[PDB]
Image 1 (cartoon, rainbow, N blue to C red):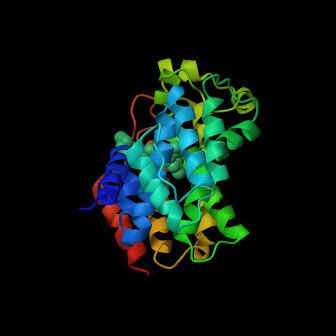
Image 2: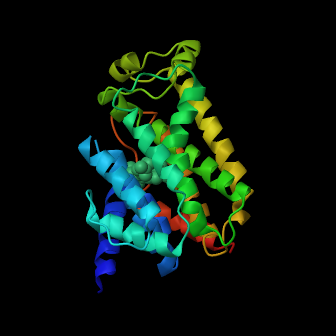
Length: 279
Ligand SMILES: CC(=C=CC=C=C(C)CC/C=C(\C)CCC=C(C)C)CC/C=C(\C)CCC=C(C)C
């Protein structure tokens, strides 16, 4: 166990801590690719939770790395991750701009006001997850064209959207609603009310209307999975398929707003089999 290794293993710990689904999937990659993904997840995880002196530190470390990839830096933030990322950046191409978007997006959240329109919601989704998918693109593809970044973005955005959908109650508890004012009003939904009195027909419909957007985006990515390298395809199929499965979970929980639903490891394993079986 070198020193890099320990850094990467911390990264890995973080990812497995916070995303049982993506770990499950992405741990099935070649060693080189799965390490890179650990580093990037961790950096992003670190920014998402960073909340404000830490976040500028993380931005500064990343600017360092981008300017002078092959210098030693005294990282202000988390040194274990920045080394792991710096190591990646030496061998692979990192969309630094996408990190800066995510960072920007996370600033703006300290004064979160509700989105006026779906457009704003989809634009948050980009900043929060579309950005991640872009950062990962060079890792999961042999040759990176515009439609490679496009797909991975679309996947990223839809997964974030599936997040929102699972997390509706929890998010309300933390004084956040991600459904847009225009869509709430059109569908006649008061999220405060549903939280108290259970679900109804108007909620289900709004929730089902977003769900439709996700499933559709998921399908659109499956039919373009080829843009990713051959080892990564079934991995990315898996990750996505597990995450759509989250939607049927919420349905069986009757769209509850008083627990995180989950896809038990056995189901995860079932799906790896279905997907693996046709590769
Ligand atoms: C938790 C989970 C997921 C979490 C988050 C996700 C996302 C943020 C997707 C979008 C983000 C992407 C592409 C990059 C990540 C980095 C940032 C967005 C900064 C599913 C697995 C279940 C767990 C770990 C236990 C939870 C308990 C239950 C399900 C009962």
